[PDB]
Image 1 (cartoon, rainbow over the protein chains, first blue to last red):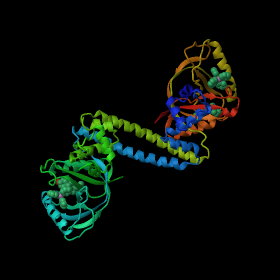
Image 2: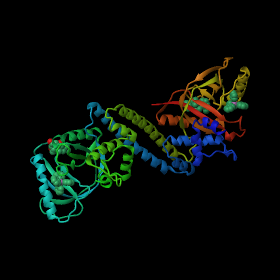
Image 3: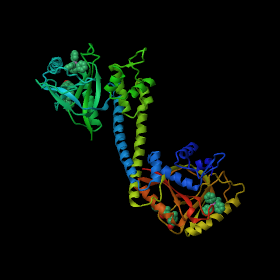
Image 4: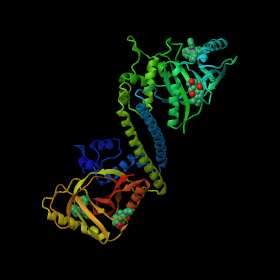
Length: 268
Length: 268
Ligand code: 118
Ligand code: 118
């Protein structure tokens, strides 16, 4: 059976048979030496059937070489079983994500906020946890802390890139009784004089959305994020953070400012 | 903020930012013409955030380059949703097949048969449907059926490759007095003579198993295939075909016989 007839028997292209010969997966029975023409037999169709049966299960080519040459190799198929289970979980989450994205673009003509699930590493921060009467009053008392901590810790260099955020330790919603904890990441340990202390903040996977503009609309992102958090079945494992990209330090106009709200979540 | 500090903000590789810049997506703010350095600003971070959100959604890069600026293009999102649904369906299929594979390999030392789905086209066959008392009498009676057909039709040329097969239109296991229909696909129309007719057999999606051995033990294969259709949640849509590829006519050794069982099947 010449390669054309055989390629139509097994119903696959010629280049596929060329490739399977090139990698040594399916070798013709008899190659004519001067022309190089490949001729197969029935016992090449018998092997191509096994090859295609394994290849419909997603096995990579080298995995098929091993599956056909090494017997009692059930650990590689089980490994592939676990990987396929992981991709099914991931694809179902993707389904929920794309349903929510389509649900939004029909709900609003503009996508104001996209939600990204990113991993944030562990940090070394100086932290002050305290009650706040008003979030507007919360903004002013931070540069005093900036003076104070650099005073008490000489030569303490903050991490680059700068990570300056807020934990919201409140389990429900209110506007004037916010129990917050301001954390900012530095390089080394330090002195703990004052309400300012040092602590290690563990690495977390968190869904974050970046809101750009003034802070009075920031709650929007939270409602959105909360929707997201409930829609895709994620569970909020820790208190929500808010990391400051743009603000009074870089830029003077308060409408081009930008913060990023981060929800610590776990997949359940 | 050079590309290193920006790549450390997003926790992304320098090569990814390079690739994005090459493709036109996420062009940086300032490319210094003396040394070609790349400086990024936080607005580029805001753009990269939605880039990373879509890349976390499964969207290919050309789809992100078309989605990040032409904000009206929405049909491409239900289209991606349909692609993901197709993949989830096929992955669930694959998962059922891998679990069935694992149970069967843990069962027996030797994997005798290996099922594979393939799309068999429609084909113009000549057919003869009739009753047989046993399998051996049937095996002996096919060749005179072929001889009668080649005599009654002058100029009848078979199709290459030779798709010559039979159908068991019974639904339960009938060992004797079988209602069997032999058929073979030909090049073009002939004239109906006797009880042999011509017709066009429609294209199917068939789960196939190649039996190597004498014909009286093809039965095993069917049971296996049956388990495969009940286990992996497929459904037998039509009478099972059995195609003869290699056998007593081409090689007189009984142990080099090849028959390709084809269950017409549909997904549930
Ligand atoms: C110590 C404590 C706070 C700040 Sb900053 C800041 C943070 C990261 C990168 C640049 C600046 C600040 C504010 C105004 C003027 C100058 C610096 C800051 C304040 C509130 C909330 C978040 C960050 C700086 C040092
Ligand atoms: C019409 C009917 C049967 C056969 Sb064949 C056969 C040939 C090629 C591929 C598959 C089957 C046959 C028999 C003798 C000499 C040459 C060809 C055949 C034989 C036994 C059982 C079933 C079919 C051929 C034409």
